[PDB]
Image (spheres, grey):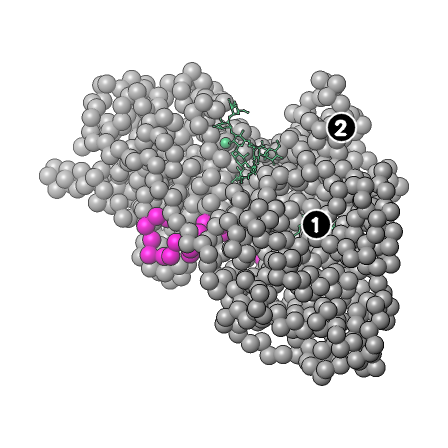
Amino acid sequence: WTATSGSCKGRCFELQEVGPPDCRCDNLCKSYSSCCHDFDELCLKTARGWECTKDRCGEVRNEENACHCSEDCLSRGDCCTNYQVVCKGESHWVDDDCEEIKVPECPAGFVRPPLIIFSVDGFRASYMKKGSKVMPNIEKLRSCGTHAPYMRPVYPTKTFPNLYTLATGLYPESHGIVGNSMYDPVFDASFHLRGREKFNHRWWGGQPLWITATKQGVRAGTFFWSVSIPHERRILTILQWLSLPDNERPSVYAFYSEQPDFSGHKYGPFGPEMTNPLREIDKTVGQLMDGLKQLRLHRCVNVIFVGDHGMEDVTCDRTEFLSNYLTNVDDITLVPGTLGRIRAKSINNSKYDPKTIIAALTCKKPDQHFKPYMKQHLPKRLHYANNRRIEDIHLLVDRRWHVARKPLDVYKKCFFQGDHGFDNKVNSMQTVFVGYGPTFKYRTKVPPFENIELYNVMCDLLGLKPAPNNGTHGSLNHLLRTNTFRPTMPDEVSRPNYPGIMYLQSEFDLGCTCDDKVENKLEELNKRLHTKGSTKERHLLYGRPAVLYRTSYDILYHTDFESGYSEIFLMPLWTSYTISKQAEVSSIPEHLTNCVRPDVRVSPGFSQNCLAYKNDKQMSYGFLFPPYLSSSPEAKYDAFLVTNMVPMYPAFKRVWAYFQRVLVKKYASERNGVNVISGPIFDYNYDGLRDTEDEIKQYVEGSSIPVPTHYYSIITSCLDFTQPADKCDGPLSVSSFILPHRPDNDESCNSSEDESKWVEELMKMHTARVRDIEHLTGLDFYRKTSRSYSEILTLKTYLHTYESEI
Ligand SMILES: *[C@@H]1O[C@H](CO)[C@@H](O[C@@H]2O[C@H](CO)[C@@H](O[C@@H]3O[C@H](CO[C@H]4O[C@H](CO[C@H]5O[C@H](CO)[C@@H](O)[C@H](O)[C@@H]5O)[C@@H](O)[C@H](O[C@H]5O[C@H](CO)[C@@H](O)[C@H](O)[C@@H]5O[C@H]5O[C@H](CO)[C@@H](O)[C@H](O)[C@@H]5O)[C@@H]4O)[C@@H](O)[C@H](O[C@H]4O[C@H](CO)[C@@H](O)[C@H](O)[C@@H]4O[C@H]4O[C@H](CO)[C@@H](O)[C@H](O)[C@@H]4O)[C@@H]3O)[C@H](O)[C@H]2NC(C)=O)[C@H](O)[C@H]1NC(C)=O
Ligand SMILES: CS(=O)(=O)c1cc(Cl)cc(COC(=O)N2CCC3(CC2)CN(C(=O)c2ccc4[nH]nnc4c2)C3)c1
Ligand SMILES: [Ca+2]
Ligand SMILES: [Ca+2]
Ligand SMILES: [Zn+2]
């Protein structure tokens, strides 16, 4: 109930909202039914259009036009954005040469350059290029400001998760908005786009930009709009807000466009109908820029132009139904679309068996267009698991296709030509980003960047301090003209031991068969120098990884590889090694095949044993420094130390082997050397953060040897590949992955063939940023380089997509 009898005489687009049932007149009163009776009248004016004709010039002010061309309009704040143009013979903004904005040029009373966040829905990355002809304003912004080729959204590439990520800098698994659709088990309730539930604040976590501004005494415009306010009125309202007396006037404002998403769903991404909704936007950007010029603000405001996701060609026929894969299709409940999520229809169903459901969905049709995962097994770069609103069963869907539950859910429950929500590394899903303003650079391209990073930029731009988020503060300094944030390397918490020889073979009892007992003054001295580290700047190019939590670990040196061995986890946390282009792969000689040797540097108490492995028919073992890539047949013995051993499933061993044996040399060739760091990853809680001892769930049977859930690798070389990895004195180049340590290869439908045909494909799928590994290992890389720390952060936010050209 609401008694909407109060008036809006004077509360037109008021900023603070009123507590029910006194009627409201803010830009959202519509969505809550509770507008003021005269709201429509007083605040949705429409007469004479949105543009000043040449006759309306210097008219007598009439209070119920939509905007005014009367001589007072400028200083009343309600001029039409083209008023100066027509009536006072001024040019449109777009018709101006871009001038470098060296210092911010603000009218007095403006403490700080205000921020305008202009968000356009579904604005695919390539619209900038393929549309430039019909978008002159948006092309000025881009070319004169600072843009990236494309901005990577987040999964799921849906509207709500992506808009609240921009405003929080948090993954959806963190803010809790994990789809446009969303059942919550604890709340017993569903969140849908149509309905009122979306308003309950209980779905929304983290601190959005607007709350962050306000908590710190920076006034914030309103960010959401009622869908019934026309865009031209939206811009007038913003320009109206800008005319407010200093202490009533917001510092950060927001525009939102339903286009081009709305059209794009109907015509596909480049339906020839699409040219026109694009023009609208550019027209609107024109109005906004024209209005800023009106107010002498146009060289003082920072505008951010940005999308939430792109659009892809998608149609009703390219739809897989599950009722073609299952039997009891009515015992589940599916969240369908460009991605499937599955759950029981009842938890009064204890006869629900998720293993069976997944099974019945794996490689079941030769050209299957989705793939089932349990949520913990999704690529870690998606960060889509650590929430109870995300169902344990997920269906990752092919670009261009849909998943639905039954045929009856599609014909009467075809029409459209485009959808969105696919894997976020897909090129059709990429969106846009330009920054124009005094605080941005002038005619400057920046590399692609994930959207999680904007919140930090926006706090910087507004003089705020960022609430804890998932971006990497400083990683986007290369965008800004001046930076509030001087980022700083985190201090090392744990210091390493550097253990010497302290044990004799006989003190060990690991049950470790080896054949190595045949063996000077020359190189009985050189090998000593290997275990001290005369080759330490050969295999550790960027300095020792920093351990950022409290533990006891050792630095073990060798001829070919350095490792940080954990006494607690009983394996290395990292192994680093250079493979120059001239490196050579070799075989594992017949006598040395089941060779596992005791490490006389580490206690038998802090070593693993071969016996637990023999007794475990589920577990085999593997090696971090590959034996295949030994420098000498003498150095090859080094790779067989029990301290280089890690546990591997036989199924995973296949993937691992091909990577070490084949791929490492491959890259080594292509990039003129690579430095490879590798190690385990323990994340049983799928939070994306390193597990500690007390949370280990799996052990190598009958031992204290914990089983990694993933294994990672960082592969770095010179960015200028004409320099050897181990002499690159310029920017770097990296690429990483985090493969799930799994006992089958059911993820890979080509598994039963040659590794040459499916491994490299599975690695590309599970690629990751160095930063992601950093969260998962609690480590910190690239400590000793010649490069700026800001440059290094950018490096670590990088994701290799293995996609084609945008
Ligand atoms: C990306 O970045 C984000 C953000 O930085 C990372 O997410 C953060 O990660 C932290 C580590 O997991 C986690 O810390 C938790 O916090 C627990 C509860 O904290 C609650 O209060 C928060 C208040 O916010 C304040 O914000 C500002 C300050 O900036 C203030 O001015 C305001 O006034 C506020 O007070 C609140 O944000 C948080 O909300 C969560 O829960 C809501 C619903 O209940 C959600 O709507 C909301 O979205 C949050 O939910 C997310 O996080 C939870 C995990 O906590 C996750 O399960 C959800 O799926 C979702 O993702 C809370 O309400 C706190 O209890 C924890 O401390 C326990 O564990 C530690 C471990 O040692 C103990 O030291 C401690 O004693 C304690 O143990 C106690 O509880 C145990 C079990 O209950 C028990 O056994 C033991 O005996 C003790 O009783 C812990 O510190 C943050 O919650 C989280 N923040 C966010 C935004 O999600 C994320 O990791 C990053 N991702 C990656 C991979 O990089
Ligand atoms: C970037 S920011 O400045 O930080 C920011 C952050 C947030 Cl959280 C919100 C905004 C402004 O948002 C609004 O004004 N809202 C109302 C209109 C809709 C979005 C929410 C369009 N919505 C659909 O319902 C829809 C659209 C496209 C779709 N494609 N497919 N389904 C769709 C559904 C509702 C700006
Ligand atoms: Ca959207
Ligand atoms: Ca964890
Ligand atoms: Zn859409």
- Near mark 1 (Cα within 10 A), the count class, few <14, some 14-19 or many ≥20, is few
State the residue position of label 2: 332
Residue 748 image position (x, y, % from top left) = 59, 37
The residue range painted magenta reads 782-804
- Evaluate if marks 2 and 1 touch, with contact meaning CB atoms under 8 Å apart: no
Q: Which mark is residue 602?
A: none
Going by the numbered disc 2, the residue's amino acid type is: Ile
Q: Is residue 752 visible?
A: no
Residue type, numbered disc 1: Gln
- Judged left or right of residue 300, residue 370 is right
The image quarter in which residue 91 lies: bottom right
Which residue lies at the image location 75% right of the left edge and 31% below the top edge? 189
Looking at marks 2 and 1 on the same chain, the residue that comes earlier in the sequence is marked by 1
Q: Write down the quadrant of residue 132 in the picture.
A: bottom right
| Rendered view: 179 above or below 303 | above
Q: Which structural element holds mark 2?
A: strand
Instruction: Single out the residue that lies furthest toward the left.
Output: 521
Residue 190, visible in the rendered structure: yes
